[PDB]
Length: 50
Length: 50
Image 1 (tube, chains in turn red, green):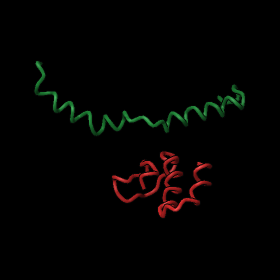
Image 2 (image 1 turned 30 degrees about the horizontal axis):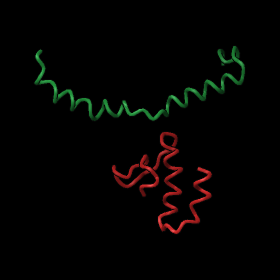
Image 3 (image 1 turned 90 degrees about the vertical axis):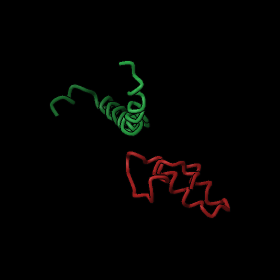
């Protein structure tokens, strides 16, 4: 998580911040929960999918 | 309070850690039993010899 958080803000991908947040969200599954949008893009998707 | 005095402090922390990991283990089995397995049993059942 440290490596990805430091490395992400340099890429030109517009969807970078969402991936940065989803990384920590994925690692938090079962410890803490958040309301997502639907049953497909749930909290346990690979952060790279967004 | 009346059982932990028999244990050293470090062992308590490790015991707390092991249980926590068991709580959050990424096991897919409970999902299988709730959503998929009944469908399989329903499909197979009529073809049974008994």
